[PDB]
Length: 281
Ligand SMILES: [Ca+2]
Ligand SMILES: [Ca+2]
Ligand SMILES: [Ca+2]
Image (cartoon, rainbow, N blue to C red; front, side):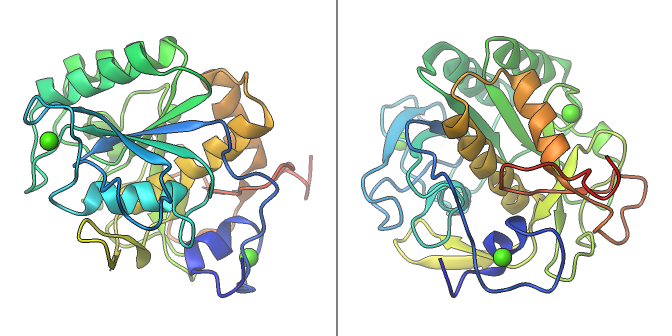
């Protein structure tokens, strides 16, 4: 609410300066976010029971507990009570990355397919992960999106063209670059024609796998801001197809706020239900 951390603070307003407030009209009630990552600590206090295990494709078991931190931190930015965007969203852990944060292409695909097969009501998927170009992984993500589930994808952190990263480059995904609280593109953020918009990703505080908290930076942290907002939009309109949700993320985004976009469309995440063309529509 107040004393809001900067990422949340930024996404409910058009312009700087920050006002230390995160205002919301929705909270993700009745929506489920599938976190395809290192797992999620279901017992973390930030979730208040709204997190449950999905499946663990690293160890082939039913317990998607997190032994790295990244997955929990991402889930916290989507749905944590203090530090999340959509404070009553449901969270499901889809563990495809090991305690060290490594995974296999085929294990990630299994997680993607699992979300397509198991999503029930209004759903969004978060993939804060990426590696080399893979047509097989691209095809699985494209398939899950055709199934009706929107996918938020990290652009990557190499200060490079996101189009050379899978799954970031999948056109029908919503691919997210990272900014700081000064509205600069984060210096590590990938960039380019495959990036759909920017969101807060530098110095983001959220839940950690040990039950405490951690502040970290990456396009991996920007992405769940966007998934969080997708959950807000899905609560507002349960029936949005991925094409409709993409359209709305675009039309509602704040325009021309970001510096050093380096060939990326100048759109920054906005969490509220009104259109960002409003200078000149
Ligand atoms: Ca604010
Ligand atoms: Ca496990
Ligand atoms: Ca896209």
